[PDB]
Image: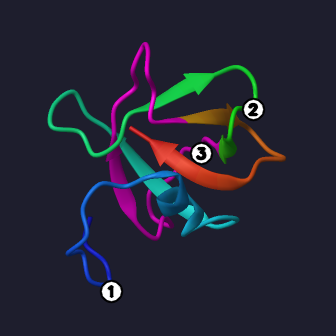
Amino acid sequence: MYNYKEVKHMGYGKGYLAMFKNKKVRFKVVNSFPDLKVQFVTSFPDYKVKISNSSSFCEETIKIQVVTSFPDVKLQKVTSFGDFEAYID
């Protein structure tokens, strides 16, 4: 999505999510031409995310799409004690 840095690069990965590690972010779950496929689990896969009910605070927004198999990046939605904060649609 839009930002201060050049958005010439395409395809986001794990490192991309680390860009805002220990910071706040926004997530937008879509059902078409998504940005990244991230599956949600009950445990802590690779990274942890904290689900919040707020929009006027996020620094950036990224489109995502929950999959059933062959997920791009797994995240753990918790209320606290997580890695970073992200508000998914």
Q: Which mark is residue 44?
A: 2
Q: Position of residue 49 (x, y in %)?
A: 65, 45
Q: Position of residue 58 (x, y in %)?
A: 48, 64
Quadrant containing the C terminus is top left
Vertical placement of residue 9 versus 50, above or below = below
Mark 3 is surrounded, within 10 Å at the Cα level, by few (under 14), some (14 to 19) or many (20 or more) other residues, namely: some
**Could you give the CA–CA distance between mark 2 and mark 3, rounded to whole angstroms?**
18 Å
Callouts 2 and 1 close, C-beta under 8 Å? no
Circle 1: element type = loop
Vertical placement of residue 74 versus 61, above or below = above
- Judge whether residue 67 is colored magenta: yes
Closer to the camera, 36 or 89? 36
Callouts 3 and 1 close, C-beta under 8 Å? no
Residue on which the image places disc 3: 52
Q: Residue at x 56, y 25 (%)?
A: 40
Q: Nearer the viewer, mark 3 or mark 1?
A: 1
What secondary structure predominates along the stretch shown in magenta? loop
Task: Say what amino acid the circle numbered 3 marks.
Answer: Ser
- Which callout, 3 or 1, points at the residue further toward the start of the chain? 1
Q: Residue at x 63, y 21 (%)?
A: 41
Circle 3: element type = loop
Q: Residue 21: name its quadrant.
A: bottom right
Residue on which the image places disc 1: 4
Mark 2 is surrounded, within 10 Å at the Cα level, by few (under 14), some (14 to 19) or many (20 or more) other residues, namely: some
**Could you give the CA–CA distance between mark 3 and mark 1, rounded to whole angstroms?**
25 Å
User: Magenta residues, as a range?
Assistant: 50-73
- Judge whether residue 37 is colored magenta: no
**Outermost residue toward the right in this view:** 81
- Which callout, 2 or 3, points at the residue further toward the start of the chain? 2
